Amino acid sequence: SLKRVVWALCFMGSLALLALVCTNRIQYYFLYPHVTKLDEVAATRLTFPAVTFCNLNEFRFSRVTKNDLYHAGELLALLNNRYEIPDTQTADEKQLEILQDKANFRNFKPKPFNMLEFYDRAGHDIREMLLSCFFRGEQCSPEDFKVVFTRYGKCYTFNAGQDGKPRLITMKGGTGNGLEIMLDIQQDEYLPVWGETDETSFEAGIKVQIHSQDEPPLIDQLGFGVAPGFQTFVSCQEQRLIYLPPPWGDCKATTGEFYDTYSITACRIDCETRYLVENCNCRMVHMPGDAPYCTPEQYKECADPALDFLVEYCVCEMPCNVTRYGKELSMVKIPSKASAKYLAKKYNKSEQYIGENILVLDIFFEALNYETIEQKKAYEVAGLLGDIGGQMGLFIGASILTVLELFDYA
Amino acid sequence: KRVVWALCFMGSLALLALVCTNRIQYYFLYPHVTKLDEVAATRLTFPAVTFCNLNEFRFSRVTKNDLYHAGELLALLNNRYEIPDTQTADEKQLEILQDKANFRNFKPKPFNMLEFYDRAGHDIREMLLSCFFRGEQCSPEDFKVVFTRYGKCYTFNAGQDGKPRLITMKGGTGNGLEIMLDIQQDEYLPVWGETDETSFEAGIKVQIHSQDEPPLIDQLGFGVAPGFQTFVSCQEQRLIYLPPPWGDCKATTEFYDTYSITACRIDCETRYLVENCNCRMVHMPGDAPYCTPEQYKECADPALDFLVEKDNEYCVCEMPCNVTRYGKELSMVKIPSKASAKYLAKKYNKSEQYIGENILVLDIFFEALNYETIEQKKAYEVAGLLGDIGGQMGLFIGASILTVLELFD
Amino acid sequence: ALCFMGSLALLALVCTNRIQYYFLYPHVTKLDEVAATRLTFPAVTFCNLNEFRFSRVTKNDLYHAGELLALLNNRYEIPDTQTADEKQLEILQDKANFRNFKPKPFNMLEFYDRAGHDIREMLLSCFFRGEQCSPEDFKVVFTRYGKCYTFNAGQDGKPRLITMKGGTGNGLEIMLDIQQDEYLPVWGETDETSFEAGIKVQIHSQDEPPLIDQLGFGVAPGFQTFVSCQEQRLIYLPPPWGDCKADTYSITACRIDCETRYLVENCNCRMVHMPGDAPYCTPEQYKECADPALDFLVEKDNEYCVCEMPCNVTRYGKELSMVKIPSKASAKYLAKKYNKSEQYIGENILVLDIFFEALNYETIEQKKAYEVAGLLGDIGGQMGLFIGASILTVLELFDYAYE
Ligand SMILES: COc1ccc(Oc2ccc(-c3nc4ccc(C(=N)N)cc4[nH]3)cc2)cc1OC
Ligand SMILES: COc1ccc(Oc2ccc(-c3nc4ccc(C(=N)N)cc4[nH]3)cc2)cc1OC
Ligand SMILES: COc1ccc(Oc2ccc(-c3nc4ccc(C(=N)N)cc4[nH]3)cc2)cc1OC
Ligand SMILES: *[C@@H]1O[C@H](CO)[C@@H](O)[C@H](O)[C@H]1NC(C)=O
Ligand SMILES: *[C@@H]1O[C@H](CO)[C@@H](O)[C@H](O)[C@H]1NC(C)=O
Ligand SMILES: *[C@@H]1O[C@H](CO)[C@@H](O)[C@H](O)[C@H]1NC(C)=O
Ligand code: NA
């Protein structure tokens, strides 16, 4: 019969086709696809971020005591392993006099010694580095900086959000309307450079990280530099990422050892911290917990090889609520010739000092808005069924109530 | 056994109600997603470039009459009308002032801050040591004056009065705009004490913006320092965002013909200041009278310092739907080289010390000949709604829209 | 059944919308970032802004190229302008005396190589992930700035280097001496003459040549410059959805090819930075033919040679930061260490520090917005909604359209 052939001829193609296309939409769904929704929304306020900054130098040269030098000199490249000064013809005369004086161990009774105490006491004091401080055109004081220990030593966090302190906000973008600090980096307190190590800088300045209050600073890896002699502008953009969990993504939605709120920085410090305690029964200045802080012998012999080997293991995925701060750096010179003499008079320093040691850091929001980056689900379940039902109710006539009629037969 | 059957219709009917209502809610969220694209081009329209010298008024162009009317405002006179004892700056300046600042037998003359701003301001004619666009030279006539919160400022390629807008045909260092600026530090007003308005900075402020929007360079600027050639690698972005209900965008288009966040902020900030003090600042549009130095101290500084905190929503300025943004990557090298310092001093009758204190080279260009497009697309249209519910009907039931119409009888 | 005519019209309406939408070939974008344990480090190409060393310029160099280089006026003599330091003006006034001189052959590629800055003397210090490296890790490549060097070229069978940690130390950390004293003196102005001093750096995939005259950034002396990178994997869509195109293709290699086919066709000449086997331009040929020939291409024949984007692309985003060099504590030491003045150090030394912010890579991918499977579901659902229709019912109406 020609018709009931041409009929079932092209109907069998149509059932193979529905079988084909319906398999495509079930395979796609099981890839669990997502797409991205970029949006920007206007705002009237914006919570100002946390700002963590460090002097590139860890210990003030003048704050080193005789006791400090006995224990830490070989650690700091100020004594060779026989405990005396190299007398290298590279030196400041006055500093090498100060050192050999403090480094003469005749009839010396070693005293107790601790690395947090050294870091805390020898570290640069915000009270003397913070020549000037203004937030939204109102004044601020070293009280507004919370101390934090990083691999760069005693560092400070503005608007840290801790100890019941509210988070600062801003109501206008641009230079005057955020944080504007004038720092004095104190170059002549830098520990001298007579030979080289992994831990030696020719660098001079500060290191800065702008980060949310829910995450600690990781300023040795996430920092940026600000150099002396310039007022450096930091124009920021608030980005609110909302990312998708598994199966759609690799997000971490949950709660999270030594911290309470999960964040990639907080996670990487745990892997670093437990590894060092497990392999050396020891922690470093930047690590949380209760372990004893490392001794100079323990660092030379144990912790440095333990970290050196650790890199050559621990994966830390992104959280689902993440607020990031994008920034555009720009800079102009300080001081102007007109203000150079005044700044020296104002702070009892020479004009040469001001241009070698003064930086102004100026952090603000470009404008009152925040960008939103959200992974959205591409193929929900409701949309699959509409797609199959439409494909069924097209290639054939079936409903799901029909396919159940085929069981009422058998 | 047909109670298993009408149980199995009542269930499958409930499932259609649930899944179909989900797509009705989703549709009512008015969802959108984003389409990133990059498209090649053979030419590319060059932006406007607005720049300001960080100093507002040239020290040498300040007259006796200026000092009488604006001297206390500018931290050049204490409220007794004299140099403030401290006098912490070099004699030749302070000598220049002690003569200009002697009001014995002085007859005050009229004064206007815009006239002062225009007249004392840095002149593009002395600032612009050199200028090249697409390797061809340019002159101060290609820069148009605009008054900003920084004063008398200059915009390259302003696009106004029927002048064609420049284009570019190649990316990289030379193939856009390269200026050598003299910021003229020896003209900066002295600093003897501090004010809200006093800076230790020296250099220029630059904003790269489309010609459809005015410069708001005291917020949207960036700094360029003297002593460097500063490279500005730009990427053109044409973002097209969606109106309500999908977004919060503005397609509608007072003080300006074309909507822009900047035009809205300057407009709102202007209406506020005129309402509360009958007074506008130099950077503001319109026809209101310009603030006098007394009106600033007595009215506008407090009026603005109060709008900084207790206000905000007098204007939320929403984004327009068709927006061109310029991304910029800043880089720099030192100018001048040891070989070219001596040549540069000779060229401009200036000291070698001066050049390293006052010369900057600004280099604005496109990374490459293309533009990115960031585009909001609707995720769930009405046509796709019907396809989704119709299929669920034609799946859980055999139902059509006509079938549900028979059930009303 | 009266208003059936309406519901059929609505099916025509909605079905035309989703059928036209399909043919726009819509795509939307999928942003994701995925964590990694290792990460392949890029190539880094850098140039001294200065092309030829003053000390390596010979009398023969000066005869053929002195006018090309604004070192001689078109009478072949020194401008004798005292606008440069005496020792160098004496060095050149000497080299420029053409009494009894037999000119010898000369080609521009040799000059670029020999007078160009030598990688062995610029590279004061080199560390990759804290381990030492040597000028042997730098492959020479010729760009418009002359003899330039590419670290981790990935060429000559060397495996591609990786890094396992982010931050300051764990990338490439070179300390350069830009050698301000070998910069050619500047006596007058040219298209090709600079007041600048420092280097130009480009971070690129090993699969593409550097286009450092267009895509570089500047590094200045007197600073350690921090370069924080983020690896981006772009996967973009071919036609009809997009305009991407699927030794190795790259946008850079496409432009350098258009630039070379054009210059050889019109001047039978190639420039130092160009690939192939054509002869290199003589100073007169550049003067007489190529300089106007390239000038013309930018204005009229960019439009004829169009270069589309590739479909698998790895980009490197960079954030520049800097701190001062050298510190007062280390200023005296670096002078002693390299037998140079403290003022020389602050005028000639930069430390370039390239690294990844952290161990992850972003992926920006164009995805198809409306495929064919999803079209049918939408129209099929619309058919089974406004009417009862399947495709079979439409075949009954063509059966019945056999009466
Ligand atoms: C308990 O916590 C810790 C204990 C020991 C640690 O090990 C070291 C810390 C610092 C240095 C070091 N800092 C220098 C600065 C300048 C110079 C210079 N001469 N320019 C030389 C320096 N050496 C060396 C080893 C680390 C810890 O926390 C990370
Ligand atoms: C009609 O429009 C306006 C009227 C008044 C305005 O008020 C002021 C404008 C400028 C200053 C100011 N700029 C200084 C720079 C350097 C120094 C220094 N001593 N170095 C001191 C300065 N004082 C102060 C007040 C503003 C207006 O429009 C914005
Ligand atoms: C076959 O390959 C080529 C041949 C010729 C080319 O043309 C020129 C190459 C270099 C210069 C040039 N470099 C200078 C550096 C310093 C100074 C200074 N006075 N300080 C002046 C300089 N002039 C000019 C023209 C280009 C080629 O390939 C790109
Ligand atoms: C966190 O995630 C929740 C999930 O619903 C979301 O509503 C909220 O906006 C996110 N942000 C904060 C700061 O809680
Ligand atoms: C965007 O702007 C251009 C010119 O301003 C105009 O031609 C175009 O129609 C506008 N709309 C879109 C969606 O591009
Ligand atoms: C390139 O695209 C292909 C898709 O066919 C993919 O398999 C591959 O991982 C991509 N990346 C590279 C580096 O080739
Ligand atoms: Na659908």
Image: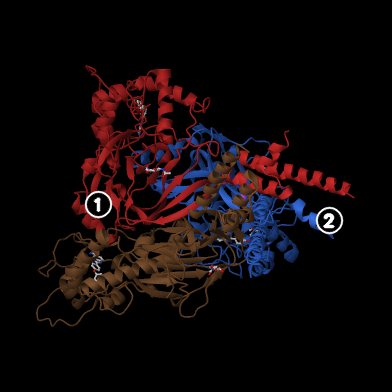
Chain colours: A blue, B red, C brown
How crowded pointer 2 is (Cα within 10 Å; few <14, some 14-19, many 20+) is rated as few
Mark 2: secondary structure:
helix
Q: Quadrant of residue C252?
A: bottom left
Which dot marks residue A408?
2
The image shows residue C208, relative to residue A224, as above or below, that is below
Q: Nearer the viewer, residue A147 or B110?
A: B110
Q: Are marks 2 and 1 in contact (CB under 8 Å)?
A: no
Q: Tell me, yes or no, if residue C259 can be seen here.
A: yes
Q: Chain of mark 2?
A: A
Residue at (34%, 69%) from the top-left corner?
Answer: C256
The image shows residue B8, relative to residue B318, as above or below, that is below
Mark 1: secondary structure:
strand
Q: CA distance from mark 2 to mark 1?
A: 86 Å
Disc 2 residue: CB within 8 Å of ligand 7: no
Q: Nearer the viewer, residue A300 or B151?
A: B151
Amino acid residing under circle 2: Asp
x, y (%) of residue B204?
Answer: 34, 43
Q: Tell me, yes or no, if residue A107 can be seen here.
A: no
x, y (%) of residue A377?
Answer: 63, 51
Where ligand 2 lies, by quadrant?
top left
Q: Nearer the viewer, residue A120 or C202?
A: C202
Amino acid residing under circle 1: Phe
Question: Would residue C355 be found to the left or right of residue B254 on screen?
Answer: right
- Quadrant assignment for the N terminus of chain C: top right
How crowded pointer 1 is (Cα within 10 Å; few <14, some 14-19, many 20+) is rated as some
x, y (%) of residue C309?
Answer: 43, 62
Q: Which residue is mark 1?
A: B132
Q: Chain of mark 1?
A: B
Q: Nearer the viewer, residue C135 or B206?
A: B206
